[PDB]
Length: 121
Image 1 (cartoon, helix red, strand yellow):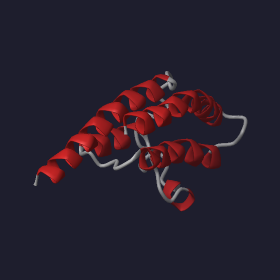
Image 2 (cartoon, one colour; image 1 turned 90 degrees about the vertical axis):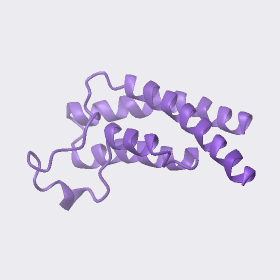
Image 3 (tube, rainbow, N blue to C red; image 1 turned 180 degrees about the horizontal axis):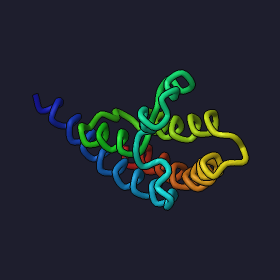
């Protein structure tokens, strides 16, 4: 149907906008602390602590399959990156601190992304 095509175009355009958001948030992590999944070979207990691991590569795979239906879903995954890190790592660590800085900086980007998603529809 033409209705199904139109919906698919909206999903494609959302995907374009989330790709640009993802790039912007990842630039706020110049250390690349959140670039890849936590290795279970290197942190064998991780899944005892963290039940839903997340990282920027995993988000990018989902994005490219057009697997985010709305901005809420995308923000959920970004929040998991931050929140997982702040639980696993102590306050005095470079990892925790990197997450705080990513959260603070990413807030700015996400605030305007919401306006744009509502605005363009």
